[PDB]
Image (tube, rainbow, N blue to C red; front, side, top):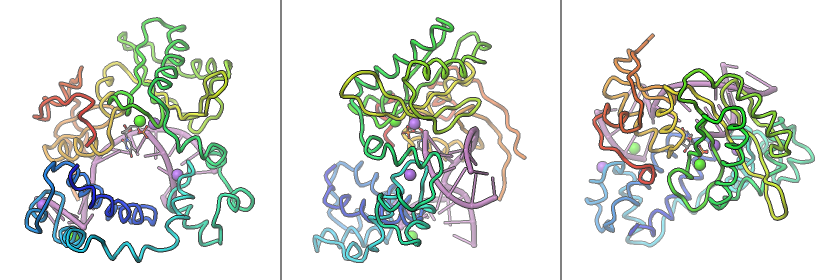
Length: 316
DNA sequence: GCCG
DNA sequence: CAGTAC
DNA sequence: CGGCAGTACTG
Ligand SMILES: Cc1cn([C@H]2C[C@H](O)[C@@H](COP(=O)(O)O)O2)c(=O)[nH]c1=O
Ligand SMILES: [Ca+2]
Ligand SMILES: [Ca+2]
Ligand code: NA
Ligand code: NA
Ligand code: NA
């Protein structure tokens, strides 16, 4: 990234817009920042900037200001509420609408939230683990967590496949959470193994809090045994074997990579989700499409006309 | 905010 | 449903 | 002008 002296400035504005609820302007800013990071050739002109995809006239003027004047004046008018809104919306379960409500009510600190705010169960758990959830763990610990869940699961059925996805699967040195995807090549055993698996993990003391409990998805909190351990975010999902590939893609991310693949699919009349890649999905402005066989991620790429990207090149 |  | 998360 | 990904728990 030869343009850090621009992305540094633009990330602040993107975050201000994001915490203040201007989701689409924040998205545009983020895509332009990805463009900047991906150029590998320091932009040294307004025409070179205005010519990069994801970067238009507004962003070109911002960048030219940063280039010549070494500073962007918009940054001097970020609302004073932004640091408080960021503090509040880093609580798991609270987003921009709750952060802004809390701000309007006069709250300015987590002590205010603790003593005065009305919290959901999820928010009370997120506040209780605030510092822990802001940390990333070494991928070695992620391995230990994956293996804990895989041992718990493979006791019910040694044929179950358990794969840790997310940044872990993209090969990052640290991970903000662990996301375990479970399936069985038999196609008809992933029923009941989910509830009993969670009962097992809870009996061992491994699971400490539940955030979301659905028929297919679990999101919660775990902690490995012993000293020097923190609480970590853990997701577990169980899927039929026929969806395994599409799950692996989706839950491996990144989020920008997925959103790009899904935009592309949408262009070619297809629809891509965590369940299936469908074709001739009818839309406008009920679209029961046809599911396409995707036994491997490579098949998803191929059906979309793309070369296969390994998980490590999927940052955006 | 960007792009069709 | 709106809000939130993935 | 208008989409910007698509799906699933909570309350
Ligand atoms: C944050 C986010 C992630 N994802 C996908 C890509 C991430 O690698 C995967 C796991 O999410 P995570 O990074 O929060 O654990 O979920 C989405 O589909 N949408 C989102 O908004
Ligand atoms: Ca991750
Ligand atoms: Ca614009
Ligand atoms: Na461009
Ligand atoms: Na939050
Ligand atoms: Na996750």
